[PDB]
Amino acid sequence: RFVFPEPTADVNYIVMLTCAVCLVTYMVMAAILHKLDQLDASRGRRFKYEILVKTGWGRGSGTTAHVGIMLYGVDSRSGHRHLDGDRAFHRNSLDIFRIATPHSLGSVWKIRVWHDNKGLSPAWFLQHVIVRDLQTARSAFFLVNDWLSVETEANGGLAALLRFRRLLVAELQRGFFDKHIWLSIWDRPPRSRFTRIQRATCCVLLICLFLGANAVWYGAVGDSAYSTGHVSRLSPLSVDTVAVGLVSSVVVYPVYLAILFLFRMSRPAWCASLAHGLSLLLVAVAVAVSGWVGASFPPGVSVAWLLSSSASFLASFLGWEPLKVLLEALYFSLVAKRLHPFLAKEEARKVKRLHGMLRSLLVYMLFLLVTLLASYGDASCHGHAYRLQSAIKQELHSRAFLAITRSEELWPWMAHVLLPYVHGNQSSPELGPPRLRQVRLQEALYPDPPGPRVHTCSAAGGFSTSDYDVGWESPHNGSGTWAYSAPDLLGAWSWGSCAVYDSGGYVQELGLSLEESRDRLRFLQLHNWLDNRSRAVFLELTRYSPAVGLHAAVTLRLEFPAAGRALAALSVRPFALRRLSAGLSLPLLTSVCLLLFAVHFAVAEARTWHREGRWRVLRLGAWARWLLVALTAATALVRLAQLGAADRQWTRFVRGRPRRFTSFDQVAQLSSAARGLAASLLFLLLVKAAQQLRFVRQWSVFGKTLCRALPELLGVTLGLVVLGVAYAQLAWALRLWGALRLGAVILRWRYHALRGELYRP
Amino acid sequence: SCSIPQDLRDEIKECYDVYSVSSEDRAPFGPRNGTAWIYTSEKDLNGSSHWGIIATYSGAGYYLDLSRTREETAAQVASLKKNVWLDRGTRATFIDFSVYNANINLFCVVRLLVEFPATGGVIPSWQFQPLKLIRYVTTFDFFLAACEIIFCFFIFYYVVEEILEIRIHKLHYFRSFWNCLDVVIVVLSVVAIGINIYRTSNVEVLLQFLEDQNTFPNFEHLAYWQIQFNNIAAVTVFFVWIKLFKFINFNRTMSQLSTTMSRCAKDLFGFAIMFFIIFLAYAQLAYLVFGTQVDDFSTFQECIFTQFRIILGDINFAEIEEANRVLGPIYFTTFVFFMFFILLNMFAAIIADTYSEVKSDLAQQ
Ligand SMILES: *[C@@H]1O[C@H](CO)[C@@H](O)[C@H](O)[C@H]1NC(C)=O
Ligand SMILES: *[C@@H]1O[C@H](CO)[C@@H](O)[C@H](O)[C@H]1NC(C)=O
Ligand SMILES: *[C@@H]1O[C@H](CO)[C@@H](O)[C@H](O)[C@H]1NC(C)=O
């Protein structure tokens, strides 16, 4: 049950972009985890009070013993190390226990003690380290005071006949956040042979296997039950949208849980390198297969595939790793019955900073993925849009229209090219008749003698608002046969050469057929429809293209600055009519996700406004983050408005299609604005991605030399601009400054200073 | 070939999709008289792909071989025009031939392409290529043959004396930039020798044409490998010339002029990434905003080359604001300010500073 698609040379960017982020986001944290586990490698060799472990109670110890203390509790676990000293608990000798036990629980039960003596056993009994309180009292002031034997073990809370009921709890508490490999990169216990660098390898293995498994069932398995693809709506169905992720995740593990065997229990000599190679091979082949099979997805299935892949991850995180943990704990508790699980504060701060950086990068990568899908998610109807825009001009004689000067050339213009283009045999499908709405201006103009064009434009007044009969003003029975046709509520403001209009004005439907179009044209030609004051003409119809699936709003306009001559301007806006009532398409998915990133980024600002209290204003951090919210919210809320306008206009047109116009133009504007915003948020993210390059040792100087020298650069440019203003006040500095090469020396001085400062350390 | 939305299906009678191998017609149309109305495959046309502007067209289609005299070729063209041969379903048209010019010994193949995008319009393209297939005539050709056998001997010597420096000598040291370059030259020369041998090992199409001179000479394949070989033999020469820097250290003033570059090539590389990230950030924004109504930003490569031309101060922004006014002049001004007065300098300052210290790092010595 399989078909080799190999359909054509098309390309799908959603699958290619999703797989190109889950690999970069891994190659980036690889360095972070290397820098983080170097510290553990070099270190593996205080909520608790000062432990009163001065063992002045034990004697007769002609041997050497070591005591391990397990700082159990909630989110705290550690052990013991070697007592570096000359005494080392020799015969009638001991010491006081104080080591790096930063993992300490709260003021609750935390005690577990073992003691092993290499050789003989002393005839003594050291009670305990009964501390009381120094910092936070992470222990209790009590003791057992029992004798020491071969592998002595003292256990308490604040011999063990039924170990099962407590071994289960101990194993569960140990492995609950250590076997759950997703959130196990942050909480690896020390002295472990798993090294935090293959924790990020199995994770990306699961990610790229989920991607491949979900990509296989869409577009490759389409014979079994025909239940795939088109028959199932891309919207959440819970019958073929969550089940696919479940099945894929379930079937993937026999490849994963077998490769973990080559990482754990691998000291089993060189299996780590072989496992790493098998991973770095499987990930690549899975990505290649995913791309090859996804390069044929229709625009409707590639959004359900993403949801299925996301839901697969939510299965490996809420019930498939927890059951693995439970099974492993049950195994360790039922078979083999295991009974075991100034320089300082500088490393803790570094580890905390590295953890914060690691948890602050996943959010950024998710944001980048969302904003990339929101903009290049349909980056295939972009060349087609340019071709359609160019082909609407080279066949409508744009150069001829833009060059007309006589206000009467309009009539031969429409009678020569417009009619043969709108009507034909099967010449360039239309989707709606044209319109000729006109604005009168009521303030008939007085011209100027001919010659050069009089500056740009002047001598204008108000606008007409009343009704007029055939010819001009003579309203006899009811309303004028040439009514005003008041502007529509939404969809106007053409913003002409030197005027701003709206959707109102005296309209002309121009008819349907070519012959009746000529009839109307000549009728209004002879009756003096356009020889008066007559500010504008506003010809605008439509265009459709089903081969690529794009609409186009076309608008041709002549403005009359003074009676006698006109200036022309045409605008062709190609867009794609995607509508809100079409389901859960990509422009809605990556418009409700962007709205969540504009809330998580807002509450994260309130939690600092309140914490820092008053007077957070007048700093970059409290302003450069509010711009991000005000940009993400606009990007999210403009696309939704465009989607709603699409439904409203489309249903209004379908209601009265044979005789109406419906002026789709406003959508062609919103669908552009929603592209301008989404193309600038990605710009900000890419700028931040370059600013965050200051974490390399020898490259951090570039940001500093730019920031410190900034005031001098602004002072110099301000001086130059005020000098230019003074020069022009009496009645080009770019060449002057570009030849002075100042900025270069200003930057060089600071660069030299910073390099000298950095050289010494 | 495409899907008509049901809402307006009463108006859209039919559609033709853009060109694709999975949506290419293969059935007779019009009068089924000759070979101009019957789909002939690529295998029996001896054709190949072209990689035009809109897409990559295959070598099949409906073809016709014109006649040898004007008065009947015109009749054939008129017959094609009368019975409509260029419907709306046509997507590409090729016209090709070749000439000899027997005074010098140099062929010339000519191909003209006209593309009809599905969104309407016409896009022309042309290609003229001066092949030469009868090389060994003049004594100068014999001299060239001798000089290229000499080149083969030289590349053999250079590959053996570079293999000798791997296992019989220094093992696995590459980070010198003078051995990483010496391998590129050898590989490129090997590729260019293989291509040249493959090109002249089969000239059977010329023999077939010379057998009977009333058919169409299918010289299209040779004209492609000639271009592919010139594209390689021109890059090898560039790197060979660049290799001359290996030997310019003949005095105590040529040594520091190279030490300066060798010591500032580590610091400039770090800043280059930061420069080109913001460069691409501007490029993609321009592509998304203006890449629909300018044609100077129609494709991403064009967006990059436009910014490189902005650096030179070549392009004029007379039409940028027409595509958009909010982001029209703002983009230009911010680009010029940030990449022509603050980011383009750091490349200078750094270098200058480096030079200075290098001089000291010698003068003290
Ligand atoms: C093309 O197909 C459509 C729908 O089948 C119909 O107009 C007609 O069959 C064809 N039109 C032509 C060949 O002009
Ligand atoms: C087909 O027949 C001859 C060639 O066989 C051709 O000249 C003629 O125009 C065609 N007949 C038609 C188109 O009716
Ligand atoms: C393709 O080459 C063969 C080789 O002899 C030739 O017979 C055939 O005519 C060629 N195809 C065409 C369309 O001329």
Image (cartoon, coloured by chain):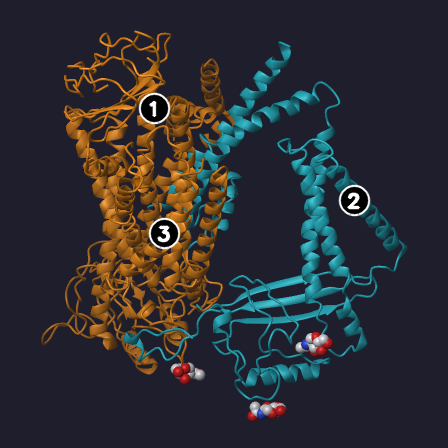
Chain colours: A orange, B cyan
The disc at residue A350 is 1
The disc at residue A253 is 3
What's the residue at 48%, 40% (across, down)?
A: A271
Query: Mark 1 or mark 3, which has the lower sequence index?
Result: 3
What's the residue at 21%, 60% (across, down)?
A: A644
Of marks 3 and 2, the one in the foreground: 3
Give residue B193's position: percent from left, percent from top. 74, 52
Ligand 1 lies under 8 Å from the Cβ of mark 3: no
Looking at the image, which is closer to me, A330 or B236?
Answer: A330
Ligand 1 location (quadrant): bottom left
Three-letter amino acid code at disc 2?
Answer: Phe
The disc at residue A582 is none
Assign a secondary structure to mark 3: helix
Label 1 CA crowd tier, 10 Å (few <14, some 14–19, many 20+)? few
Label 2 CA crowd tier, 10 Å (few <14, some 14–19, many 20+)? some
Could you tell me how far apart the alpha carbons at marks 3 and 2 are, in whole angstroms? 53 Å
The disc at residue B156 is 2
Q: What chain letter is assigned to the residue under label 2?
A: B
Ligand 1 lies under 8 Å from the Cβ of mark 1: no
Q: What chain letter is assigned to the residue under label 3?
A: A
Same chain under badges 3 and 2? The reply is no
